[PDB]
Image (spheres, coloured by chain):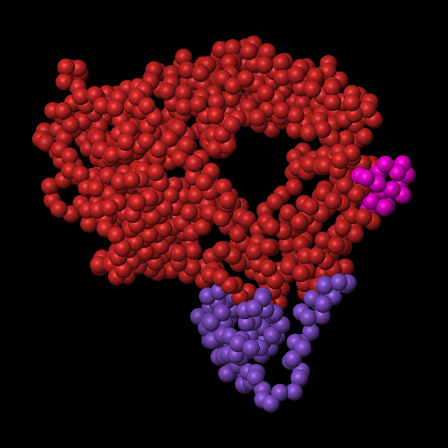
C-alpha cells in the first residue's frame, strides 16, 4: 500500500495516537459483566434512532427459543470489540461516545 | 340552444376543475357533473364560470377499461368526497375510478360545450338566465395574459403510531412507505387535525405566512390575510339536473395562476392537511354546495409510480407543480411543466393513458390499422413474437477493427409510428369526437424535436399506451420488423453491413479505405441519405403517413467495435480518443467509477493492439486488466466510510431485505418514497451483513462498518463480464477473466 492508502490503513487499523499516552485520569467505561450489558443496552438504544441495527438477543427462560442459545458469556466481548473498532465518519463523535458518555474519545 | 340571448365574451381559461357530481331525479344509466372554470380577461381579472355535463354509463365503462363499474359506485364516492372532515382521502380506495371519472368528464365537456384549451383566447357564450356557459369557440383578439406563479413552502408534522405503518406494510410486502403513511392518515383522519404546520406562500404582490401549533387552534404566528390571496365568490346557477336554484361558493386566485413547490422535501400529507383546513373553515356557513375534495399522485398506489406529481381534481381549483430543486435549470423545468399542463389539458399525468384514447377503444383502432396495411406486413404482424430475432447479424463476444463503424438512429420512431397508425385506424372509431384526443398526440409528435418536455411526455406515454392494449404492441413490433427488413435490404447496396440494432437505432460497418479520412465521410452521408429515402418510401407504401418528416441521425463515426452481449457494446475511435459504452448497469454512485475504469482499461487494451504482436499481447492485456482491478479496489478503500456511495437502488419489482422496525420511526422522511429505495449493507457483528435503508433515517448516520466486500464483489462481477468478452472477442481466447478478490485484497475490509 503506497500513498494516502498507507496512512489511511495505519490510522484505521491501529489504536488512536493518543490512546496509549499517559494522562492524569482515565476516561473509559469499566464495570462488571451485567452492568456492562446494561450500559451496552442503553447505548444501543441511544444509537438505534440513527441507523444502528438492533441486537435482538435471546435468553433462557424466554417465551421463544429460536436459534443461537449461548447466554451472556461471549456476547458481551464481541459487541464491545465491534464498538471499539468503529471509526468516526468525520467531525462527529464515534459510536463508543454513546457508551463512555464523553464527546472527546 | 337559442342564440338570441347568448352573451358572448372574450376571455381565457386557466384551470378546469371538478366541482360536483350528482344523479338527476330519475336516472339509472347516466349522471350529471358540474365543473368550474377559472377564467381571465385581457388585462388580468379573475372570473368564475360553471358548466354542466351529462355522462352516460357506456362512456364510464369505456374509460374505466373494464365492465365492473356502475353509476352508483361513482355517485356514492363523489358524495363521500364532499366532506373532507371525515374522508379526506377518498381516491385512495380506488384511484382508477377517479381517473376514469376525470377523463370521462373532460371528454364530455370537450364534446358537448365545444373545443376548450387552457391559456388560449376563447369566445365564451353563456345563458344569463341559467348562469352556465353553453358554448366555447376559438377566436383571436390579441395576446392573452401571461401565467403567474406563486412559491409554496408547506411543512407538517403528523404523528402516526409506527405500529399501524408496520401492520399495513406487513399486509402488502412490497408497499411503498408513502402509501402506508397516506393509508394510516386515512384510517384515523384526526391525526391531520392535531398536526403542527408552517405555510409560506410568496406571490408577486403579497406574502402569506402562517404557523399553526395545532391546526384546530388559531395560529401562533401570522403574516398577511386570506383575503389577499383568494377571493370568495358566491354564484347562483339553475342547472337542468336540479329542480330548484343551486348556489356555489368558490375560491378565486388573485395575481397568480398556479403554485410551484420545490421538490427537495415534498410531502403530500402536508398539502392535504392544509387544503382540508381551508375547506373546513371556508365551507362552514350553511347555504351553499360543497366541492369535491380529491387529489391524485404516485403515493395513492401501493407500488408507487416513477413520475412524481400532485394532481388536484377538485378543491381548491388551481394546479400545483412539484419541481426538483438544486438544478440551475429550475426555470426551464417549471416552464416545461406549465407547457405540458397547458398542451395536454391538465389531465396528464393523472389520467395516464386515457388522455389519448379510452382503453376500450384501442382494440378496434389496432384491428383497422392492421387490416389496411399490406399483405406481407399483415403476415409479419400476425406472426410477431417479442423474443424474436430478424436482423442483428452479429453475436456474443466479437470485435471489428480497424474498420469504419457507424451508428444511426431514428429519433422517436415509436411515437411517430403510433401517431401514424392511430390516424389509420381512426376510421374504426365509433365515436367521431374521439379524434381530438389523437390530435393532442399529433401535437406532441410535432413538438418532440425542439421541446424536451414533449419528448419526455411521449417517452412516458407510449409504453403506457402499449401496456393498455397488447395488440398495439404487436402491431408496432410488426411494422418495426418490416422497417428493419427494408433497412437491411437497402443497406445491402450502399457499401454497408448492419452489425446490430433493433430498427429505431442501429450500427454497422462500411467498406472503404481505412486510412483515407477524406473519402470515408463522403460514403457515410450517402448511406444515410439512401437509408432515409428507402425507409420513407417503404413507410409511404403501406399508406402510413407521418407528420414530422423522417430524419435519420448519425450518432458518430468510430473505428473499433467490441460486443460482449446482446445489449452491451463498446465503440472507439483511434484518431481522437472518443468512445461510447453501452450495456453497463448503473444502480449507484459506485458504478460510475467502475464504468470509467472499464472505459479507460478498454482504451489502453485496444490501443496496445496496433503493435501487431502474437498471443503475448493477450498476456499483456490480462496484466493491464488485473492492474486496473487492483487500482479500482485500492481507490475504493478511501470511501469505505461513505454510506451513500455504496447504496444501491431497488425498484418495487425486485426482492429486497425486510424493513427494520426503526425505519418506521422516520416520520416526514417516509413521504418521499414514490418509486425507488436506496439500500446499503453493513456488518453489525460476526458475518451478519444486514441491510439498511439509507434515506429513512435523519442525518448524520451512525452505522457499523460498511460491507464493502459484498458491493465490490457485485461490481467486480460486471467488470469481469465485459473484460472476459473483450478478451474472447479481440484475441479469440477461451479463458474466463477472474480476479482473485478473496486471496488478494479481501483483508482490507475484514
Q: Position of residue A32 (x, y in %)?
A: 54, 85
Q: Position of residue B714 (x, y in %)?
A: 65, 51
Q: Position of residue B311 (x, y in %)?
A: 35, 39
Instruction: Report whether A42 appears left or right of B132.
Output: right
Magenta stretch prevailing secondary structure:
helix
Compared with B247, B695 (above or below) is: below
Most distant residue in the left direction: B244
Compared with B708, B236 (above or below) is: above
Instruction: Report whether A25 appears left or right of B198.
Output: right
Drawing shade for chain A:
purple
Q: Is residue B667 visible?
A: yes
Number of numbered discs: 0
Residue at x 59% of width, y 69% of height: A88
* The residue stretch that appears in magenta: B606-622
Compared with B105, A87 (above or below) is: below
Residue at x 66% of width, y 49% of height: B593
Residue B608 lies in the magenta-colored region? yes
Quadrant containing the C terminus of chain B in the rendered view: bottom right
Residue at x 32% of width, y 38% of height: B257
Quadrant containing the N terminus of chain B in the rendered view: top left
Which one is in front, B36 or A37? Answer: B36
Residue B692 lies in the magenta-colored region? no
Q: Position of residue B348 (x, y in %)?
A: 39, 33
Q: Is residue B67 visible?
A: no
Q: Residue B362's quadrant in the figure?
A: top left
Drawing shade for chain B:
red
Amino acid at each position: 500500500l503506497d500513498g494516502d492508502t498507507a496512512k489511511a490503513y495505519l490510522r484505521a487499523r491501529t489504536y488512536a495516537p493518543g490512546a496509549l499516552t499517559p494522562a492524569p485520569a482515565y476516561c473509559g467505561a469499566v464495570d462488571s459483566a451485567t452492568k456492562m450489558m446494561g450500559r451496552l443496552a442503553d447505548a444501543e438504544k441511544l444509537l438505534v434512532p440513527r441507523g444502528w441495527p438492533a441486537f435482538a438477543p435471546a435468553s433462557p427462560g424466554e417465551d421463544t427459543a429460536g436459534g443461537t442459545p449461548p447466554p451472556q458469556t461471549c456476547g458481551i466481548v464481541k459487541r464491545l470489540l465491534r464498538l471499539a473498532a468503529t471509526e468516526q465518519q468525520g467531525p462527529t463523535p464515534p459510536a463508543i461516545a454513546a457508551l463512555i458518555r464523553n464527546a472527546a474519545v | 340552444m337559442d342564440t338570441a340571448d347568448i352573451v358572448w365574451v372574450e376571455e381565457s381559461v386557466s384551470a378546469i376543475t371538478l366541482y360536483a357530481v350528482w344523479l338527476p331525479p330519475r336516472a339509472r344509466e347516466y349522471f350529471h357533473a358540474l365543473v368550474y372554470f377559472v377564467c381571465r380577461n385581457a388585462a388580468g381579472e379573475g372570473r368564475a364560470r360553471f358548466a354542466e355535463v351529462s355522462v352516460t354509463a357506456t362512456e364510464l365503462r369505456d374509460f374505466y377499461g373494464s365492465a365492473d363499474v356502475s353509476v352508483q359506485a361513482v355517485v356514492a364516492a363523489a358524495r363521500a368526497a364532499t366532506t373532507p372532515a371525515a374522508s379526506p382521502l377518498e381516491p385512495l380506495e380506488n384511484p382508477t375510478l377517479w381517473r376514469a371519472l376525470y377523463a370521462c368528464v373532460l371528454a364530455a365537456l370537450e364534446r358537448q360545450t365545444g373545443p376548450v384549451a387552457l391559456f388560449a383566447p376563447l369566445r365564451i357564450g353563456s345563458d344569463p338566465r341559467t348562469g352556465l356557459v353553453v358554448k366555447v369557440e376559438r377566436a383571436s383578439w390579441g395576446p392573452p395574459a401571461a401565467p403567474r406563479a406563486a412559491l409554496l413552502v408547506a411543512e407538517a408534522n403528523i404523528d402516526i403510531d409506527p405500529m399501524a405503518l408496520a401492520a399495513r406494510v406487513a399486509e402488502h410486502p412490497d408497499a411503498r412507505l408513502a402509501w402506508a403513511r397516506l393509508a394510516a392518515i386515512r384510517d384515523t383522519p384526526q391525526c391531520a387535525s392535531a398536526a403542527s404546520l408552517t405555510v409560506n406562500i410568496t406571490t408577486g404582490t403579497a406574502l402569506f405566512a402562517r404557523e399553526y401549533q395545532t391546526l384546530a387552534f388559531p395560529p401562533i404566528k401570522k403574516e398577511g390575510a386570506f383575503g389577499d390571496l383568494v377571493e370568495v365568490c358566491e354564484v347562483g346557477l339553475r342547472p337542468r339536473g336540479h329542480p330548484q336554484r343551486v348556489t356555489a361558493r368558490v375560491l378565486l386566485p388573485r395575481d397568480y395562476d398556479y403554485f410551484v413547490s420545490a421538490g427537495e422535501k415534498f410531502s403530500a400529507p402536508a398539502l392535504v392537511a392544509l387544503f382540508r383546513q381551508w375547506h373546513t373553515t371556508v365551507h362552514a356557513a350553511p347555504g351553499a354546495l360543497a366541492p369535491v375534495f380529491a387529489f391524485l399522485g404516485p403515493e395513492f398506489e401501493v407500488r408507487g409510480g416513477p413520475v412524481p406529481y400532485f394532481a388536484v381534481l377538485g378543491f381548491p381549483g388551481w394546479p400545483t407543480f412539484t419541481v426538483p430543486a438544486t438544478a440551475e435549470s429550475a426555470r426551464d423545468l417549471v416552464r416545461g411543466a406549465a407547457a405540458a399542463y397547458a398542451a395536454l389539458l391538465g389531465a396528464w399525468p393523472a389520467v395516464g393513458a386515457r388522455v389519448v384514447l379510452p382503453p376500450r377503444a384501442w382494440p378496434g383502432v389496432a384491428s383497422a390499422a392492421a387490416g389496411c396495411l399490406l399483405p406481407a406486413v399483415r403476415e409479419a404482424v400476425a406472426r410477431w413474437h417479442p423474443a424474436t430475432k430478424i436482423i442483428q447479424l452479429l453475436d456474443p463476444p466479437a470485435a471489428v477493427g480497424p474498420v469504419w463503424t457507424a451508428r444511426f438512429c431514428f429519433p422517436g420512431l415509436r411515437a411517430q409510428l403510433l401517431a401514424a397508425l392511430a390516424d389509420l385506424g381512426g376510421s374504426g372509431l365509433a365515436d367521431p369526437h374521439g379524434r381530438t384526443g389523437l390530435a393532442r398526440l399529433d401535437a406532441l409528435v410535432v413538438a418532440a424535436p425542439s421541446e424536451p418536455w414533449a419528448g419526455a411526455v411521449l417517452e412516458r406515454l407510449v409504453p403506457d399506451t402499449c401496456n393498455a392494449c397488447p395488440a398495439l404492441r404487436q402491431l408496432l413490433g410488426g411494422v418495426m420488423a418490416a422497417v428493419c427488413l427494408q433497412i437491411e435490404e437497402t443497406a445491402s447496396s450502399v457499401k454497408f453491413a448492419v452489425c446490430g440494432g433493433d430498427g429505431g437505432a442501429f450500427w454497422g460497418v462500411f467498406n472503404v479505405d481505412p486510412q483515407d479520412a477524406d473519402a470515408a465521410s463522403g460514403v457515410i452521408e450517402d448511406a444515410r441519405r439512401a437509408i432515409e429515402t428507402a425507409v420513407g418510401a417503404v413507410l409511404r407504401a403501406n399508406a402510413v403517413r407521418l407528420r414530422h418528416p423522417l430524419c435519420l441521425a448519425l450518432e458518430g463515426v468510430y473505428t473499433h467495435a467490441v460486443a460482449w452481449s446482446q445489449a452491451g457494446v463498446w465503440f472507439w475511435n483511434s484518431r481522437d480518443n472518443t468512445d461510447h459504452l453501452g450495456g453497463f448497469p448503473l444502480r449507484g454512485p459506485a458504478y460510475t467509477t467502475a464504468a470509467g475504469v472499464v472505459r479507460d482499461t478498454l482504451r489502453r487494451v485496444l490501443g496496445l493492439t496496433t503493435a501487431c504482436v502474437p498471443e503475448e499481447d493477450a498476456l499483456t492485456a490480462r496484466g493491464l486488466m488485473e492492474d486496473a482491478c487492483d487500482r479500482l479496489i485500492l481507490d475504493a478503500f478511501n470511501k469505505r466510510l461513505d454510506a451513500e456511495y455504496w447504496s444501491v437502488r431497488v425498484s418495487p419489482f425486485e426482492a429486497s431485505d425486510p424493513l427494520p422496525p426503526t425505519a418506521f420511526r422516520g416520520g416526514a422522511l417516509l413521504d418521499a418514497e414514490h418509486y425507488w429505495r436506496r439500500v446499503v449493507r453493513v456488518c453489525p457483528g460476526g458475518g451478519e451483513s444486514v441491510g439498511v435503508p439509507v434515506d429513512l433515517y435523519p442525518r448524520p448516520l451512525v452505522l457499523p462498518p460498511v460491507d464493502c466486500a459484498h458491493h465490490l464483489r457485485e461490481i467486480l462481477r460486471e467488470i469481469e463480464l465485459v473484460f472476459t468478452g473483450v478478451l474472447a472477442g479481440v484475441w479469440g481466447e477461451g479463458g474466463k477473466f477472474v480476479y482473485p478478490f478473496d486471496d488478494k485484497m479481501s483483508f482490507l475490509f475484514a
